[PDB]
Amino acid sequence: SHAGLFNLCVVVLIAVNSRLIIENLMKYGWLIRTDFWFSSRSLRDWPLFMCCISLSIFPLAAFTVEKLVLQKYISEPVVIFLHIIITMTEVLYPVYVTLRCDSAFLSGVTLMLLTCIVWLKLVSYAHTSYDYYVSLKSLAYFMVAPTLCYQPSYPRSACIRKGWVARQFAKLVIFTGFMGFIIEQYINPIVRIERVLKLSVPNLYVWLCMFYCFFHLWLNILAELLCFGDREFYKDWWNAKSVGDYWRMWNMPVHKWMVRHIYFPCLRSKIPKTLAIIIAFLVSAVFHELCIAVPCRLFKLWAFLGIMFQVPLVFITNYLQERFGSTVGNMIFWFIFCIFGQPMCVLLYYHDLMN
Amino acid sequence: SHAGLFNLCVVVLIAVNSRLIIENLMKYGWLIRTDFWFSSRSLRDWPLFMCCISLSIFPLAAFTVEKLVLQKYISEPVVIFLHIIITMTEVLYPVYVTLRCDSAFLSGVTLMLLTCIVWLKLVSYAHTSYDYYVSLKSLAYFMVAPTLCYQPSYPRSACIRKGWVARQFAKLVIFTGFMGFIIEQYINPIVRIERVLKLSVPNLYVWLCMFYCFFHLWLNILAELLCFGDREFYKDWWNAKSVGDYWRMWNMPVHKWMVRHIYFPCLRSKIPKTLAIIIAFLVSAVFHELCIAVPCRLFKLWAFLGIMFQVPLVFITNYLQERFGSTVGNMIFWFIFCIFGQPMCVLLYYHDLMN
Ligand SMILES: CCCCCCCC/C=C\CCCCCCCC(=O)OC[C@H](COC(=O)CCCCCCC/C=C/CCCCCCCC)OC(=O)CCCCCCC/C=C\CCCCCCCC
Ligand SMILES: CCCCCCCC/C=C\CCCCCCCC(=O)OC[C@H](COC(=O)CCCCCCC/C=C/CCCCCCCC)OC(=O)CCCCCCC/C=C\CCCCCCCC
Ligand SMILES: CCCCCCCC/C=C\CCCCCCCC(=O)O
Ligand SMILES: CCCCCCCC/C=C\CCCCCCCC(=O)O
């Protein structure tokens, strides 16, 4: 029920290194100096964080495709064409903003992540129903809601616990600081066969702390502050028998965005392989490549090819899970997630950024 | 439900070191050389493993205190005196065997562990009921049963699954070999403030692998071969809010041996502190000191004082868990279990053995 071994990992990586106090060298307010964003309100990161506010205008377009009634100057291919156009400019504008304006790493990462999330929300709004109104602020709650499925009707009318979520925010900032410490003093000295695994041992813990920061801490804080309900935002992916089992429980918001893309809304095409393994993962590869490669300002297509090489890993690991046990299935998931996977998909870009 | 992060730890400590194959130097059948027992059927370990067979004769005595009916030549203090005597000689004979006969470490460890388990089984038989028979082989099943409570009546009338248990035995031998590898190449080079934690980081993983070997693997194999049922042999101790909570779910056999020692069979004395914290833990300290110090053949009383100083940690950590959070309570449990606890309670004796 609780965390358990995560607190063990945190305290043992505190205990391994000699910085037992927050003052490492001198005058450090946190346990690490501010290395994630730093600077101030300057022109380096000014258009990147002002672009995310611009991502509010694309839901505001899409409601004005649907709040415009369908007998009022719009026809049946026109509304789909407007939906495709207002999603495509929504993707293409922050890419141009991040590539033109030279900036840091994390500001581009959060702008691009917000762009991908807003895109998935937009596509889930566009095709989810039958065809001045009474629901004009439903899209303004779905924008800052964790789910990627429209008309949730999940109970907002509840007592907001101002407590617990505050503790969760403290856990969030201290684990982001722990992420920064592991990055600064475990991976940065390495950059300037088994050496790849020696390089990739700390970034697996960095990804584990990333998942604890976003899906358990941040997504529950977001579901609590606007009192969504703190719902199931993932299942037990850490005991993934296969990597295809990993993809269906690491992200319960994205998986419900996939069900319209796989089941009865998309069951009119009747194809097993491309509809689940290729184009549903082409979506995730595009919105991985945009999230990792555009902030580094070099396009080597490594995150895209990493996810597209992780696509045959589904077919290999499901059969290897059927062949071997659920133990060796999870061990081969952890090894294939460590050395050729999502942590290494940011290790390559970090090495290309810091060299 | 599954293991999850344990397979991650196994594969990441495989990936850290360069021995990616079982042939480390030359001719190694396992992934470590045979260092646990080794030798052969020689006179060094001959009386130690022949003493465990002798531990069968003390249940065979105790049934002959109870199959001898209380109207047949025995009175009410005499049966209790016979019970005390046949438990005390049961403890004191393998101590003399291990101390007189100079031998290895693990043979003494398994002899003393069997002595402690047989003692707890004997005490839980002497006082568990009201007062040639029809149940003459019940004590010969309780001897090789995981529980420490008498008259279980748990269903042996079931089909033994020959599968899974075999897989569990393969997991057991490979995790014992992985234990030997971590001991050989992570702790042995260290022996000849933060240096104590640098010494005690691999032994926490060694204890984690010991718990996975004994309580999840070996005890389920034992409960399968005799088709006991593979019952609850521990609960989630890894998310212990306190060490006082850790002691009640690390060992569900020992905890039910403690419930008769605390509740209604032993509630006639009505004392809160000594009946739960001192003399219910003096048992565990004595049968820790017999297990770790007698095989090392030096009596520095370190495991006994380690458990007895681990006793006030219950009183500190219950209030510190009421004060701080369940996250910080688990982190302080993991730190207080790492540096001054059961893994360090074998680290001191291993340092004194290998130097
Ligand atoms: C006049 C005054 C001026 C106006 C003032 C206005 C303020 C301006 C603007 C603010 C933004 C605009 C707000 C508009 C949209 C609101 C959306 C929102 O609030 O959250 C909704 C969303 C969560 O998305 C994120 O948070 C992502 C961002 C988190 C990144 C880190 C960011 C730190 C943040 C701030 C730093 C500030 C600190 C000080 C520095 C300041 C100096 C520089 O939830 C979902 O729906 C998703 C659920 C579905 C999951 C999708 C798939 C899962 C994907 C990934 C898993 C991998 C994640 C790894 C994480 C990568 C990084 C390690
Ligand atoms: C004519 C032919 C000759 C005659 C042939 C006969 C053979 C003679 C004899 C064999 C024994 C006598 C059998 C008689 C009794 C049977 C009892 C039995 O079988 O198990 C019952 C018991 C389990 O106890 C153990 O196994 C403990 C032993 C495991 C130790 C390792 C041992 C490896 C074993 C063998 C090695 C051999 C390999 C080849 C080498 C050979 C060359 C040298 O279960 C419970 O009830 C307990 C549940 C309650 C829990 C109590 C509290 C929890 C405590 C601790 C947690 C910490 C554990 C740390 C682990 C310590 C190590 C790091
Ligand atoms: C090694 C240094 C790490 C620095 C921080 C990490 C930077 C990149 C982090 C995450 C990239 C995106 C991961 C999740 C992608 C899914 C996004 C989506 O599907 O829309
Ligand atoms: C660091 C090297 C490790 C070598 C193997 C470990 C040797 C000792 C292991 C366990 C000792 C006993 C631990 C549990 C004691 C409980 C016994 C009881 O309550 O009867």
Image (cartoon, coloured by chain):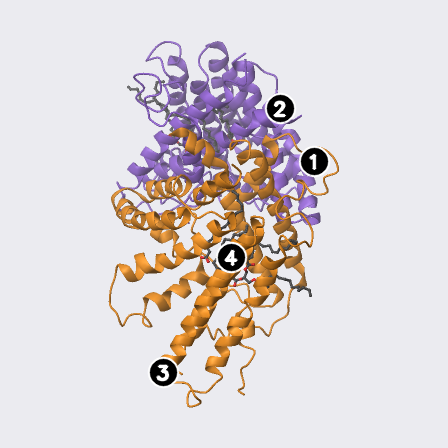
Chain colours: A orange, B purple
Tell me the chain of label 2.
B
Describe the element under mark 2 as helix, strand or loop.
helix
The residue tagged 2 is: B195
- B108 vs B241: above or below: above
The residue tagged 3 is: A76
Name the residue type under label 2: Arg
- Within 10 Å of disc 1 (Cα), the crowding (few <14, some 14-19, many 20+) is few
Query: Is the Cβ of the residue at disc 1 closer than 8 Å to that at disc 3?
Result: no
The disc at residue A112 is 4
Would residue B281 be found to the left or right of residue B2 on screen?
Answer: right
Tell me the chain of label 4.
A
Tell me the chain of label 1.
A
Please indicate, yes or no, whether residue B344 appears anywhere in the rendered image.
no
- Cα–Cα gap, marks 2 and 1: 15 Å
Please indicate, yes or no, whether residue A188 appears anywhere in the rendered image.
yes
> Which is nearer the N-term, disc 3 or disc 4?
3
Let me know if marks 2 and 1 both belong to one chain. Answer: no
- Cα–Cα gap, marks 2 and 3: 72 Å
The disc at residue B210 is none
Camera-nearest label, 1 or 4: 4
- B323 vs B203: above or below: below
- Cα–Cα gap, marks 1 and 3: 64 Å
Q: Nearer the viewer, residue B14 or A200?
A: A200
- Within 10 Å of disc 2 (Cα), the crowding (few <14, some 14-19, many 20+) is few
Describe the element under mark 4 as helix, strand or loop.
helix
Query: Is the Cβ of the residue at disc 2 closer than 8 Å to that at disc 1?
Result: no
> Which is nearer the N-term, disc 1 or disc 3?
1
